[PDB]
Length: 157
Length: 157
Image 1: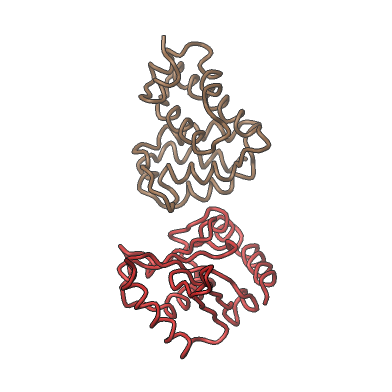
Image 2 (image 1 turned 120 degrees about the horizontal axis):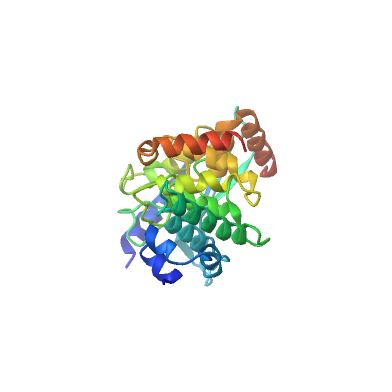
C-alpha cells in the first residue's frame, strides 16, 4: 500500500499503481485545488511517471482527469494562472520568481495531449498552449514525438 | 544605508528637470512627512506618434533598491499593460533593466524611459513576459493591433 503524499514526494510508476484502483480520486481529493501553484505541482509530478504502457498510461490519464476536472470546475479557480504557472514550471515561459524547470517534458506533454481532449478542458486555453509548445525551446526539441502529437491534437480543439 | 543611491538620484532628478523628452513625466513620490522619496518615482510614457500607441499616456512606477546604481530600477506599469514584454504584474522587461544583461550603473532614467517607449511598438517576441499578448500577436496581428489601439485610447490623457 501507499499514500498520496509519499507518491508526490518521490513519484514513480509503481508508487502510482500502488495507490490502488481509486488512485485517481485520491490524487484529486488530497490536492488543494484552490491553489493554482499546487495544482501545477501535482499535475507535473503525476505526469512525470507517464509511460507508454497500458496500466501506467491509464493511471496517469485518469489521475490528470480527476485532478484537473476538480480544479477547472471551480468557478473561482483561475485557469489562466494555472496555464501561466504550468508554462513557467515547464521552462517555456519566463517568470519573475525563480523556479526549477523539470528536466523531462515527455510525461507533461503526453498528459496534456490527453487533457486537451476532455470536456472539462477550457478551450480558451488551447491557443495559449499552442503558442508556447510551437515556440522554439531546447526542452521541447528533445521530446519531438510527444511534442508533435500534442500539437496535432491542439489543431483539432 | 542608501546614501550612494540617494546622491545619484538627486542628480538624476536635477538633470531630468533641466531637460527631458516632451510628453514624458518622471517625478519622485512623497513620503508621509512631505519629504521627497527618491527611491520611488511615478512616471508616464507617451505613445509614439505614428504608432497604434499614439495618443495614450502610460503610467509606470520606478523603484530603486538601496544598492542602486549597482542594480537597475524595477519598472512596473500601473495598471498592467497588454504587451508581450510586460508581466501580468506590470513589470516591464528590457535588457538594459537586467543586472546580468545590459544594465550598467551609468544608464539614465531618460534612457530607460525612451527604451521602454521604443519597446511599446517594437516588442521582443523571442522572450515574452506574458502568454496572452504573445499568443495574440503571433496568431492574429490585426487583432493584436486592434487591442493595442483600444488600450491606447483607453489611457488617453
